[PDB]
Length: 217
RNA sequence: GAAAUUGUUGAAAGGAAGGGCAUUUGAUCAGACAUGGUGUUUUGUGCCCUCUGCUCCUUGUGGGUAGGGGAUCUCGCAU
Image (cartoon, rainbow, N blue to C red; front, side, top):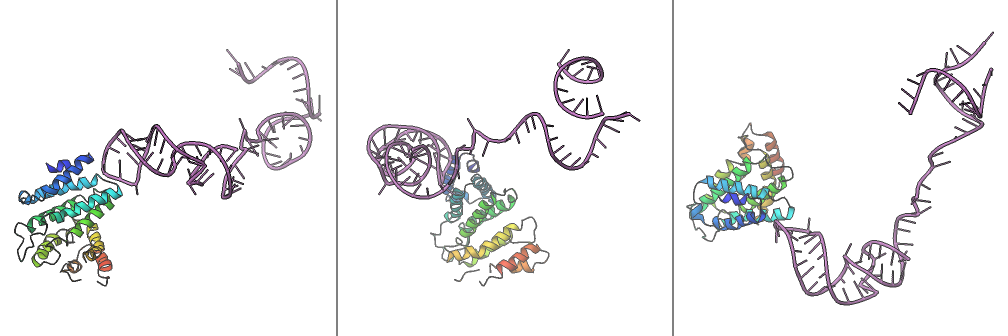
Protein backbone atom coordinates (compact mmCIF):
# COMPACT_ATOMS: atom_id res chain seq x y z
CA UNK A 1 0.00 0.00 0.00
CA UNK A 2 0.96 3.68 -0.11
CA UNK A 3 1.73 3.62 3.62
CA UNK A 4 4.56 1.16 2.97
CA UNK A 5 6.68 3.75 1.16
CA UNK A 6 5.87 6.51 3.66
CA UNK A 7 7.21 4.34 6.51
CA UNK A 8 10.24 3.05 4.57
CA UNK A 9 13.69 3.40 6.12
CA UNK A 10 15.20 4.98 2.97
CA UNK A 11 15.00 8.76 2.67
CA UNK A 12 14.65 8.61 -1.11
CA UNK A 13 11.67 6.25 -0.87
CA UNK A 14 10.08 8.33 1.90
CA UNK A 15 10.36 11.56 -0.11
CA UNK A 16 9.09 9.87 -3.28
CA UNK A 17 6.13 8.60 -1.25
CA UNK A 18 5.16 12.16 -0.32
CA UNK A 19 5.79 13.38 -3.87
CA UNK A 20 3.40 10.75 -5.23
CA UNK A 21 0.93 11.38 -2.40
CA UNK A 22 0.75 15.05 -3.40
CA UNK A 23 -1.20 13.80 -6.45
CA UNK A 24 -2.73 10.65 -4.93
CA UNK A 25 -4.52 13.03 -2.53
CA UNK A 26 -5.56 15.51 -5.24
CA UNK A 27 -7.08 12.43 -6.95
CA UNK A 28 -10.13 13.09 -4.76
CA UNK A 29 -12.50 10.82 -6.70
CA UNK A 30 -10.23 7.92 -5.73
CA UNK A 31 -9.98 9.08 -2.10
CA UNK A 32 -13.72 9.71 -1.61
CA UNK A 33 -14.05 6.43 0.27
CA UNK A 34 -14.03 4.98 3.79
CA UNK A 35 -12.24 6.85 6.56
CA UNK A 36 -10.14 3.77 7.38
CA UNK A 37 -7.93 4.46 4.36
CA UNK A 38 -7.39 8.04 5.53
CA UNK A 39 -6.54 6.78 9.02
CA UNK A 40 -3.99 4.35 7.58
CA UNK A 41 -2.48 7.09 5.40
CA UNK A 42 -2.12 9.40 8.40
CA UNK A 43 -0.60 6.55 10.41
CA UNK A 44 1.97 6.15 7.64
CA UNK A 45 2.64 9.89 7.67
CA UNK A 46 3.15 9.60 11.44
CA UNK A 47 5.98 7.13 10.87
CA UNK A 48 7.35 9.26 8.02
CA UNK A 49 7.63 12.21 10.41
CA UNK A 50 9.01 9.91 13.12
CA UNK A 51 11.85 8.91 10.79
CA UNK A 52 13.29 12.47 10.72
CA UNK A 53 14.94 13.90 13.85
CA UNK A 54 16.87 16.92 12.55
CA UNK A 55 15.66 20.44 13.45
CA UNK A 56 15.60 22.19 10.07
CA UNK A 57 14.54 19.17 7.94
CA UNK A 58 11.78 18.27 10.39
CA UNK A 59 10.38 21.79 9.96
CA UNK A 60 10.59 21.32 6.19
CA UNK A 61 8.59 18.09 6.43
CA UNK A 62 6.14 19.63 8.91
CA UNK A 63 5.32 22.61 6.70
CA UNK A 64 4.54 20.40 3.70
CA UNK A 65 2.52 18.01 5.87
CA UNK A 66 0.46 20.96 7.09
CA UNK A 67 0.08 22.32 3.56
CA UNK A 68 -1.24 18.93 2.46
CA UNK A 69 -4.55 19.97 4.03
CA UNK A 70 -4.70 23.02 1.76
CA UNK A 71 -3.68 20.89 -1.21
CA UNK A 72 -6.78 18.76 -0.53
CA UNK A 73 -9.60 20.37 -2.52
CA UNK A 74 -7.87 23.69 -3.14
CA UNK A 75 -10.53 26.44 -2.77
CA UNK A 76 -10.53 27.26 -6.48
CA UNK A 77 -14.17 26.16 -6.69
CA UNK A 78 -15.35 29.18 -4.67
CA UNK A 79 -18.40 27.37 -3.32
CA UNK A 80 -21.04 30.12 -3.38
CA UNK A 81 -23.55 28.83 -0.82
CA UNK A 82 -22.83 25.17 -1.60
CA UNK A 83 -22.75 22.49 1.09
CA UNK A 84 -20.05 19.89 1.89
CA UNK A 85 -21.13 17.65 -1.04
CA UNK A 86 -18.07 15.67 -2.19
CA UNK A 87 -15.74 18.60 -1.38
CA UNK A 88 -15.57 19.32 2.37
CA UNK A 89 -16.80 15.98 3.72
CA UNK A 90 -13.72 14.25 2.29
CA UNK A 91 -11.41 16.76 3.98
CA UNK A 92 -13.32 16.20 7.22
CA UNK A 93 -12.36 12.53 6.97
CA UNK A 94 -8.68 13.45 6.59
CA UNK A 95 -8.90 15.79 9.59
CA UNK A 96 -10.57 13.08 11.68
CA UNK A 97 -7.92 10.55 10.69
CA UNK A 98 -5.12 12.94 11.63
CA UNK A 99 -6.55 13.45 15.12
CA UNK A 100 -7.25 9.74 15.58
CA UNK A 101 -3.66 8.87 14.66
CA UNK A 102 -2.24 11.60 16.89
CA UNK A 103 -4.32 10.58 19.91
CA UNK A 104 -3.74 6.84 19.48
CA UNK A 105 0.05 7.17 19.11
CA UNK A 106 0.63 9.95 21.66
CA UNK A 107 2.48 8.11 24.44
CA UNK A 108 4.62 6.26 21.87
CA UNK A 109 6.44 9.54 21.14
CA UNK A 110 9.85 9.67 22.82
CA UNK A 111 11.10 12.64 24.83
CA UNK A 112 13.19 14.13 22.01
CA UNK A 113 10.59 13.56 19.27
CA UNK A 114 7.84 15.30 21.26
CA UNK A 115 8.82 18.72 19.90
CA UNK A 116 8.58 17.41 16.33
CA UNK A 117 4.98 16.31 16.87
CA UNK A 118 4.12 19.56 18.65
CA UNK A 119 5.38 21.47 15.60
CA UNK A 120 3.48 19.12 13.27
CA UNK A 121 0.20 19.56 15.15
CA UNK A 122 0.77 23.33 15.24
CA UNK A 123 1.21 23.39 11.46
CA UNK A 124 -1.84 21.18 10.91
CA UNK A 125 -3.93 23.41 13.17
CA UNK A 126 -2.69 26.45 11.23
CA UNK A 127 -3.80 24.82 7.96
CA UNK A 128 -7.12 24.09 9.68
CA UNK A 129 -9.29 27.15 10.35
CA UNK A 130 -7.48 28.48 7.28
CA UNK A 131 -8.98 25.89 4.92
CA UNK A 132 -12.65 25.27 5.58
CA UNK A 133 -13.88 27.36 2.69
CA UNK A 134 -11.54 29.75 0.87
CA UNK A 135 -11.06 31.27 4.34
CA UNK A 136 -12.26 30.73 7.91
CA UNK A 137 -15.69 32.36 7.61
CA UNK A 138 -18.30 29.69 6.88
CA UNK A 139 -21.41 28.78 8.89
CA UNK A 140 -22.04 25.17 7.83
CA UNK A 141 -18.34 24.34 7.43
CA UNK A 142 -17.53 25.68 10.90
CA UNK A 143 -20.48 23.81 12.41
CA UNK A 144 -19.43 20.52 10.80
CA UNK A 145 -15.76 21.01 11.72
CA UNK A 146 -16.68 21.89 15.31
CA UNK A 147 -18.90 18.83 15.66
CA UNK A 148 -16.21 16.61 14.09
CA UNK A 149 -13.43 18.13 16.23
CA UNK A 150 -15.15 18.99 19.53
CA UNK A 151 -15.99 15.31 19.97
CA UNK A 152 -12.37 14.08 19.73
CA UNK A 153 -9.72 16.45 21.13
CA UNK A 154 -11.53 18.87 23.49
CA UNK A 155 -14.32 16.57 24.73
CA UNK A 156 -12.60 16.36 28.15
CA UNK A 157 -15.22 13.85 29.35
CA UNK A 158 -13.51 10.79 27.90
CA UNK A 159 -10.18 10.04 29.65
CA UNK A 160 -9.15 7.90 26.65
CA UNK A 161 -7.68 11.06 25.07
CA UNK A 162 -4.73 12.47 27.00
CA UNK A 163 -5.21 16.03 28.25
CA UNK A 164 -1.77 17.05 26.98
CA UNK A 165 -3.15 17.57 23.48
CA UNK A 166 -5.91 19.88 24.82
CA UNK A 167 -3.21 21.75 26.76
CA UNK A 168 -1.18 22.29 23.58
CA UNK A 169 -4.33 23.33 21.71
CA UNK A 170 -5.11 25.87 24.44
CA UNK A 171 -1.54 27.18 24.29
CA UNK A 172 -1.45 27.54 20.48
CA UNK A 173 -5.03 28.44 19.51
CA UNK A 174 -4.70 32.20 20.00
CA UNK A 175 -1.10 32.21 18.75
CA UNK A 176 -2.11 30.58 15.46
CA UNK A 177 -5.46 32.35 14.97
CA UNK A 178 -3.76 35.76 14.89
CA UNK A 179 -1.51 34.36 12.14
CA UNK A 180 -4.56 34.38 9.84
CA UNK A 181 -4.82 38.19 9.99
CA UNK A 182 -10.37 40.86 13.05
CA UNK A 183 -13.73 39.08 13.18
CA UNK A 184 -13.98 35.30 12.93
CA UNK A 185 -16.26 32.47 14.11
CA UNK A 186 -13.95 32.29 17.15
CA UNK A 187 -18.71 29.70 18.77
CA UNK A 188 -15.34 27.94 18.81
CA UNK A 189 -14.82 29.05 22.43
CA UNK A 190 -16.15 24.55 23.57
CA UNK A 191 -13.97 25.74 26.44
CA UNK A 192 -17.01 27.09 28.28
CA UNK A 193 -18.69 23.70 27.89
CA UNK A 194 -15.54 22.01 29.21
CA UNK A 195 -15.58 24.29 32.26
CA UNK A 196 -19.30 23.67 32.78
CA UNK A 197 -18.85 19.90 32.32
CA UNK A 198 -18.20 18.82 35.90
CA UNK A 199 -16.05 15.75 36.70
CA UNK A 200 -13.67 16.72 33.86
CA UNK A 201 -9.89 16.84 34.32
CA UNK A 202 -9.24 19.59 36.84
CA UNK A 203 -5.80 20.23 35.31
CA UNK A 204 -7.34 21.00 31.91
CA UNK A 205 -9.96 23.26 33.51
CA UNK A 206 -7.28 25.19 35.39
CA UNK A 207 -5.11 25.50 32.28
CA UNK A 208 -7.96 26.81 30.13
CA UNK A 209 -9.05 29.21 32.88
CA UNK A 210 -5.53 30.60 33.29
CA UNK A 211 -3.96 30.66 29.83
CA UNK A 212 -7.08 31.06 27.66
CA UNK A 213 -9.68 33.12 29.54
CA UNK A 214 -7.04 35.48 30.97
CA UNK A 215 -6.18 36.89 27.53
CA UNK A 216 -7.73 40.22 26.57
CA UNK A 217 -8.89 38.67 23.28
C1' G B 1 63.71 -21.64 47.40
C1' A B 2 59.96 -18.73 53.67
C1' A B 3 59.44 -19.71 58.72
C1' A B 4 60.75 -22.40 63.20
C1' U B 5 66.50 -23.16 63.80
C1' U B 6 71.87 -22.49 63.19
C1' G B 7 77.28 -19.74 62.15
C1' U B 8 79.84 -15.08 60.46
C1' U B 9 80.20 -9.42 59.56
C1' G B 10 78.07 -4.69 61.28
C1' A B 11 74.94 -1.44 64.50
C1' A B 12 72.82 -1.22 69.35
C1' A B 13 72.10 -2.27 74.05
C1' G B 14 72.94 -5.41 79.02
C1' G B 15 69.29 -11.27 88.11
C1' A B 16 65.42 -9.78 81.62
C1' A B 17 62.33 -9.08 77.59
C1' G B 18 57.84 -8.01 75.12
C1' G B 19 53.42 -3.47 73.58
C1' G B 20 51.01 1.84 73.57
C1' C B 21 51.15 8.05 73.66
C1' A B 22 54.84 12.13 72.17
C1' U B 23 59.80 13.30 70.50
C1' U B 24 65.62 13.79 69.97
C1' U B 25 69.93 11.31 68.07
C1' G B 26 72.16 7.39 64.59
C1' A B 27 71.44 4.89 59.96
C1' U B 28 68.59 5.16 55.66
C1' C B 29 64.54 6.03 51.61
C1' A B 30 61.47 9.35 48.54
C1' G B 31 61.77 14.48 47.21
C1' A B 32 58.98 17.59 39.01
C1' C B 33 64.14 14.76 31.42
C1' A B 34 58.13 21.14 35.10
C1' U B 35 61.33 24.68 32.06
C1' G B 36 55.54 26.90 31.19
C1' G B 37 51.19 30.82 30.09
C1' U B 38 49.66 35.80 27.94
C1' G B 39 49.84 40.38 24.14
C1' U B 40 52.71 42.36 20.95
C1' U B 41 57.04 42.65 15.66
C1' U B 42 59.77 40.53 11.24
C1' U B 43 60.08 36.24 7.96
C1' G B 44 58.48 30.58 5.54
C1' U B 45 54.66 27.53 5.22
C1' G B 46 49.34 24.80 5.29
C1' C B 47 43.89 22.57 6.20
C1' C B 48 44.86 30.28 4.64
C1' C B 49 42.83 33.89 0.06
C1' U B 50 41.29 33.12 -5.22
C1' C B 51 40.43 30.01 -9.64
C1' U B 52 39.60 25.18 -11.79
C1' G B 53 38.07 19.86 -10.25
C1' C B 54 36.88 14.71 -8.21
C1' U B 55 34.45 11.74 -4.50
C1' C B 56 30.48 9.36 -0.22
C1' C B 57 25.74 9.32 1.46
C1' U B 58 21.32 11.12 1.45
C1' U B 59 19.34 16.51 0.92
C1' G B 60 21.69 17.65 5.34
C1' U B 61 23.93 24.23 10.42
C1' G B 62 28.08 17.93 5.81
C1' G B 63 32.72 14.88 5.28
C1' G B 64 36.97 13.17 2.32
C1' U B 65 40.51 14.42 -1.63
C1' A B 66 43.24 17.10 -6.08
C1' G B 67 45.86 20.86 -10.05
C1' G B 68 47.38 26.34 -11.14
C1' G B 69 48.61 31.56 -8.66
C1' G B 70 51.03 34.85 -2.18
C1' A B 71 52.74 36.29 1.75
C1' U B 72 46.37 41.30 3.88
C1' C B 73 48.88 37.42 7.50
C1' U B 74 47.98 35.27 13.46
C1' C B 75 42.94 31.42 10.53
C1' G B 76 47.07 27.52 12.70
C1' C B 77 52.00 26.25 12.86
C1' A B 78 57.73 27.34 12.88
C1' U B 79 61.04 31.18 13.56
